Image (cartoon, rainbow, N blue to C red; front, side):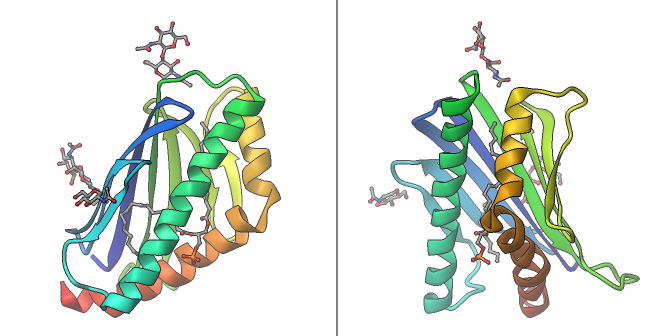
Length: 173
Ligand SMILES: *[C@@H]1O[C@H](CO)[C@@H](O[C@@H]2O[C@H](CO)[C@@H](O)[C@H](O)[C@H]2NC(C)=O)[C@H](O)[C@H]1NC(C)=O
Ligand SMILES: *[C@@H]1O[C@H](CO)[C@@H](O[C@@H]2O[C@H](CO)[C@@H](O)[C@H](O)[C@H]2NC(C)=O)[C@H](O)[C@H]1NC(C)=O
Ligand SMILES: *[C@@H]1O[C@H](CO)[C@@H](O)[C@H](O)[C@H]1NC(C)=O
């Protein structure tokens, strides 16, 4: 519906062993799969939407996102008490409404099936979704809000890159 939605589920049995499963849909059709442990992560386009050189660039940046994501969970563990095993769910995307002056974009993170933090994209700030203050949540937010990587680069990815991908490829669906 002029939208790209991406889902990443990350199963941590311990800080150093993670299992990934995810997928992306474009206009409500499955277009990408994420699969495998950190030791060997498969990231696939089901439909050849990007040309080889282009997709290879996109794929390298996804792998790099994963490495930094994993580093942040180990850091939270390394600095606060983080109880494993745990499952993290990242749900993110962009939507072009027919009646919209702006894309709607989002990035929502849950832990163990409960709301944890989410991204306020235009101001490029992360917020807690948990009702109670927690050293884990507070420390995570401190990390997410302190660096350009998790603020301004992510805003660009959701507002610019995702939206330009929808405009460029929805007609294929
Ligand atoms: C990723 O794949 C999962 C698994 O198929 C999708 O989850 C399904 O979502 C639909 C809603 O449209 C439900 O009817 C199913 O019950 C869900 N399945 C499971 C196992 O939970 C998910 O929507 C996909 N996400 C993308 C591509 O962004
Ligand atoms: C996420 O869920 C798992 C399982 O539901 C939690 O693991 C439990 O942790 C407590 C204390 O660390 C143990 O007494 C239980 O036996 C564990 N259960 C299992 C199945 O291993 C985990 O602690 C949760 N983590 C967070 C951060 O919510
Ligand atoms: C990684 O896993 C995929 C799963 O299909 C496999 O095809 C590929 O050969 C593996 N690559 C490695 C182990 O370097």
